[PDB]
Image 1 (cartoon, rainbow, N blue to C red):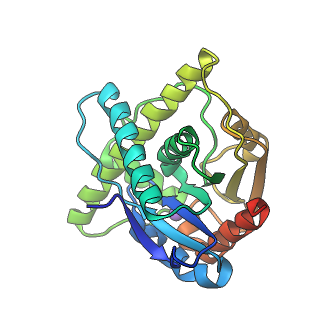
Image 2 (cartoon, rainbow, N blue to C red; image 1 turned 120 degrees about the vertical axis):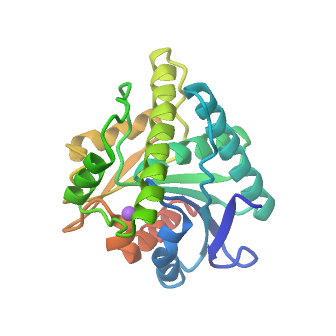
Length: 253
Ligand code: NA
């Protein structure tokens, strides 16, 4: 019934915690390999994965309400589990919920010290809804290098969850763009790391656009993973665990 799951370390002995939001259509399972690397690459950091219930909602307003509910539930469970300094991690579309979680942690005066986002850039314009067909999505994801299920059952579940996560992230970022249009989005004094595979085709012009994360927090740091595409949790999970360890090192004081 908890919104989070302990995947590595032990909060009774750790020096910090990282709470992790999965890529589109993903969940804690997508972090298994990364978690297995944490004791070696990030010894002092315990790791929680966020469960994505994909609560049914009937409007953009209800989706935003759901983002708030889910982020609040994650903060509830995290702070109930640990007082340790916290790093928030997200891959790709999970960035939306990660931002919400980070902002709520800041609102609660929790000891949140960094935001680390893989394979995503800040959105500064109202987005476009996804009207592609299922075959169009699968062709696009295949070209981008995604892993895709072969069983039609798994394909249907994947496409449902992918469409849901894209809707959630579009609604949340559109909300942030609205706030920014009124000067109502406060930058938080939380450093931001943007981790990008140099061959990632979904973050165009990231060497310049990564700095847009400064609408969220500051300072902003870019780290490039040469030879890697968009799927950092699949193709260099040890490197991302190490990235979390490095963040902790940077914010440990
Ligand atoms: Na990935």
